[PDB]
Image (tube, rainbow, N blue to C red):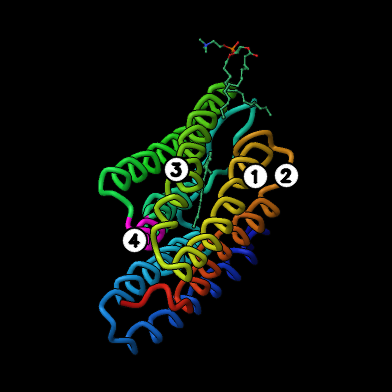
Amino acid sequence: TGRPEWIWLALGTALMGLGTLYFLVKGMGVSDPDAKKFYAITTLVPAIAFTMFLSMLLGYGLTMVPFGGEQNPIYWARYADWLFTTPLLLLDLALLVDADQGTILALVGADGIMIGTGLVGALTKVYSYRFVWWAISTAAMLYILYVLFFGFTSKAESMRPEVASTFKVLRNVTVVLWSAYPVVWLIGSEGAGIVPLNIETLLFMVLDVSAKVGFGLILLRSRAIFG
Ligand SMILES: CCCCCCCCCCCCCC(=O)OC[C@H](COP(=O)([O-])OCC[N+](C)(C)C)OC(=O)CCCCCCCCCCCCC
Ligand SMILES: *C/C=C(C)/C=C/C=C(C)/C=C/C1=C(C)CCCC1(C)C
C-alpha cells in the first residue's frame, strides 16, 4: 500500500525509541543533581523525536504544496520535532560551559527564527520565494554556529580541561551535522527537487539519529556532567 520512505521512518522510530529507553534507565540510576539535569534534558530530546517519527510512519504530519507547476509532498511534522529539540540541544551546550542568561535567550530566539522561517519556506507557493525564506533560515543558523564556535569555546576555556574537551567534541559534532541540513533542503523535495523524497528521508534520519542519540551517548558517558 504505502510510500517508499516508510522503511527509514520505521528505522528512525526504532533508533530514537531504544536511545530514549537507554537514557531513561541510566538516568534514573544516578543521584548527582547536576548529572540528573543533563539526563532529563537529553532523554527528552529523542523522546520527542520518537513521537514525531511514529506519527509520520502512521501517515500524519504530511501535506501537499503547489509550486513549480505540480503538487509536492512536504513533511511538516519534522518542523514540530526540531522546534523543541534544537533548543534543548543548545541548552545542554550552554549548561556545560556556564553561558550567560542573555546569550541563551539570544540563541533560543535565533533557533526559533531558523525553524519558523524554514517551515514558512517549506509551505510557500511562489517557487522563488521558497528560497528567500531558506536564506533567512540559513543566516539564523550561521549566527548560532558562530556563537557556539567563537563565544562558547571562549567560555569553555575557563572550565576544567575535561569539561572543555567534552564541549569541544560536542561542538564539533554539532557544527558538522547542523551545517548539512540547509544543503539537503536545497537539493531535495523542498527545494530543487533533485534528490527524491525517499533518499532525502534517509539523509535526515541519519543526521537526526547522529545529532540526538550520538550526541547523547557522548555527553552522558562523560565525567563532565557530574557535580
Ligand atoms: C545564506 C544567505 C545567503 C543568500 C542571500 C543572497 C544570496 C544571493 C542571492 C541573490 C540571487 C537572486 C538575485 C537574482 O538573481 O534575481 C532577482 C530575483 C528575481 O526573482 P523574481 O523575478 O521572482 O522576483 C523578485 C522580486 N521581489 C523579491 C521583490 C519579489 O529575486 C528573488 O525573487 C529572490 C530570490 C533570491 C533570494 C534567495 C537566493 C537564492 C538562493 C539559492 C537558490 C538556489 C537554486 C537551486
Ligand atoms: C535533531 C535535529 C537537529 C539537530 C536538526 C537540525 C536542523 C537544522 C539545523 C535545520 C536547518 C534548516 C536550515 C538551515 C534552512 C532550511 C530548513 C532548516 C530547518 C532545515
Gap in Å between the C-alphas at discs 1 and 3? 23 Å
Gap in Å between the C-alphas at discs 4 and 2? 38 Å
Quarter assignment of residue 42 = bottom left
Q: Amino acid at mark 2?
A: Val
| Residue 147 - label | 3
| Residue 95 - label | 4
Verify CB contact (< 8 Å) between mark 3 and mark 4: no
Viewer-nearest residue: 173 or 86: 173
At mark 1, the secondary structure is helix
Verify CB contact (< 8 Å) between mark 4 and mark 2: no
Q: Nearer the observer, disc 1 or disc 4?
A: 4
Q: Residue at x 48, y 34 (%)?
A: 137
Q: Amino acid at mark 1?
A: Val
**15, above or below 29, in the image:** above
Residues shaded magenta: 91-98
| Residue 195 - label | 2
